[PDB]
Amino acid sequence: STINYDLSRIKALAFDVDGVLSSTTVPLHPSGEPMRTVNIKDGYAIQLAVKKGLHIAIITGGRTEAVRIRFAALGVKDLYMGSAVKIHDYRNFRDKYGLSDDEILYMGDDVPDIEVMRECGLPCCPKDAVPEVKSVAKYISYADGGRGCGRDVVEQVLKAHGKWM
Amino acid sequence: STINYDLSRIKALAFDVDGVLSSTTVPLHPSGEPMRTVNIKDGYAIQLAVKKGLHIAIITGGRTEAVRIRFAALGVKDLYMGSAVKIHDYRNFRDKYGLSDDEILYMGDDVPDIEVMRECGLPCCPKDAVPEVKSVAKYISYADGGRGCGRDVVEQVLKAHGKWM
Amino acid sequence: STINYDLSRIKALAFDVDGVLSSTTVPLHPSGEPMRTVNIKDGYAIQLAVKKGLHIAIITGGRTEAVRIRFAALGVKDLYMGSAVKIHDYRNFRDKYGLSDDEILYMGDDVPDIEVMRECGLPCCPKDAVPEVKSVAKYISYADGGRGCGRDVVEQVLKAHGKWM
Amino acid sequence: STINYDLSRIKALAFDVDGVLSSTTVPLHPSGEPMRTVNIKDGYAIQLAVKKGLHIAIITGGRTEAVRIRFAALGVKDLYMGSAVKIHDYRNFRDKYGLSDDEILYMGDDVPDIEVMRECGLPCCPKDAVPEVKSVAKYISYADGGRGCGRDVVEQVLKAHGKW
Ligand SMILES: [Mg+2]
Ligand SMILES: [Mg+2]
Ligand SMILES: [Mg+2]
Ligand SMILES: [Mg+2]
């Protein structure tokens, strides 16, 4: 669905990992660390978004190594991991590029994402985000976490800039 | 749907792993041992529950270091792995904290869980639990095993205590 | 649903692996070999069946150690792997135990299973089996392949024998 | 068949991997490399098609040895990998066998597949292909990417050849 926001002023998109770029339910590695998922259609749009000049960030509380490598390989340079207080890292990201809050989209799925979602210009969440998160979101994707909700908003922003084709 | 029970009486929540906190269908590791899944929304609620003073136990026949690690990383201290007859680990958990049965929730999915479910105050099960288990459950989650039925009940109990942050 | 057959007469149950006890869509191991999935509810019933004196076989074109190890661990001794022409292995299984066709259930999902299904007394298939297989099946499980169709039929047969609870 | 095309004309089927023969959402290997999925019903039909003399190609931007070995093991002899320019793989595949466009089916799921789909005779896509891909597809499978959309078209073509 189209987002209730002037997407033309979005210059940056930030994402939670678990329940957003990765599925909420994932296999467990023998090591005890979650084996995350990535969505290939998410991937296409994200690498394109980086090529077209949008600042992309991931902000996660874990040390999700495999996710770091994958998105690094997509050109994403702002990878905030072990983010115990996400709002502090969001601020770092915003200020690093001299952005205003109204220029940043953030997509989260669970309560540790709420503080950022309250400060960012365009809070978004997947179709299966928790109710507390849906109530703070300006847009709720048609797609569940890990299954194309990233592709959804990235494609919308790129199209609105005429940078999709 | 709220659980038909006075959740303020619940001081402890115990979970089967396979089919409850981990999906019923899982990848088979090349070793021939099943690879459990974890749900990150479950995880958030579980770790918060521990912090808020709810007692949390997992009780599983499984012996994999992955499951032990993952739950110990959430602050679960009562990890009953390699469980042969679950009722004993249930009693152990109950008695360790001076609980009565009516103060304990147990969530199971299959026949080996029935004995504990008959004894605990608040038996539940996921949406896709087996008939005999649904039969004895006071509450059936809206979520399938591994897909957030853990999150469901932990949150409900935390909310009823005024501890849902 | 329930099987339209006199299950008290069934003395043995044989299963294809891929697409029946394992999902049709599976992760690809880096070695180039498809991984398999297993279902924990299938497992409980299968190990129970062996304990209740029912003859259990798997008949698969696959050859992976993981599959062999997993089913052996459930106590399954009739492991027909690398099965190129399944009818030979079905007949070997039947004649091994002096069974007649009407005493054997076989569950398959694809064309290579059809010959065995035409011969066994009780051919079954998962909900997502191919239409040619559904055409020869006397029973279609409510469950997709890998997701509990094994449990479905094993449990029905054990209950018929009064060997469930 | 239920595809609106004379499938007996199709002599070759080419498939994108990710989002078509492998699922769109996949597990991540600890190396940071996505782990593809395969569908066992796709597999049976693919190996049969090869046996019945249909030309099969897989066209993918990836380079993983796993996808290489798997499809090789199914008898697939035309494995286009490491590719970025899909139209070139398609044209090379077509010309290798002296085919005309109308004799080739191609199934893709995303924007980079569009150029090929506009050139091939029978462009198909999975049920969850992006909307731009759906608008150029002659046929949209009932199956999601990685979940039997390959089996769908291969089987329909083999049936129309009387080779099923
Ligand atoms: Mg999250
Ligand atoms: Mg269980
Ligand atoms: Mg099969
Ligand atoms: Mg693709």
Image (cartoon, coloured by chain):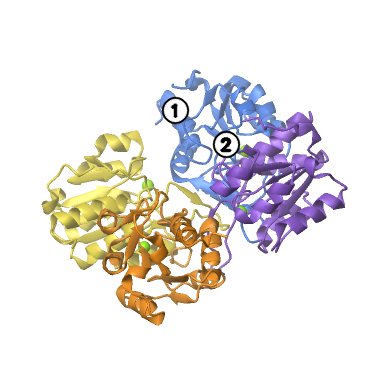
Chain colours: A purple, B orange, C yellow, D blue
Amino acid carrying label 2: it is Tyr
- The chain ID associated with circle 1 is D
List the residue tagged with mark 2.
A142
Quarter of the rendered structure image containing ligand 2: bottom left
Report if residue B121 is visible in the image. Answer: yes
- Where is residue B80? Give x, y as percent: 42, 75
Q: Are marks 2 and 1 on the same chain?
A: no
Q: What crowding class fits label 2: few (fewer than 14 Cα within 10 Å), some (14-19), or many (20 or more)?
A: some
Q: Left or right: B149 with respect to C151?
A: right
**In the image, residue B36 above or below residue A118:** below
User: Which quarter of the rendered picture does the C terminus of chain D lie within?
Assistant: top left
Q: Secondary structure at mark 2?
A: loop
Foreground residue, B142 or D20? Answer: B142
Mark 1, other Cα within 10 Å: few <14 / some 14–19 / many ≥20: some
Q: Which residue shows up at 48% across the image and 40% down it?
A: D147
Q: CA distance from mark 2 to mark 1?
A: 32 Å
Picture quarter with the N terminus of chain D = top left
Task: Decide which of A58, D95 is in the foreground and name it.
Answer: A58
Residue C91 pos. (x, y %): 22, 53
Q: Nearer the viewer, mark 2 or mark 1?
A: 2
Identify the residue under disc 1: D156
Task: Answer with left or right where residue C84 lies relative to residue D14.
Answer: left
Residue D33's mark?
none
Does the rendering let one see residue A129? no
Image point (11%, 53%), residue name: C8
Q: Nearer the viewer, residue D42 or C85?
A: D42
B9 or B74, nearer to the observer: B9
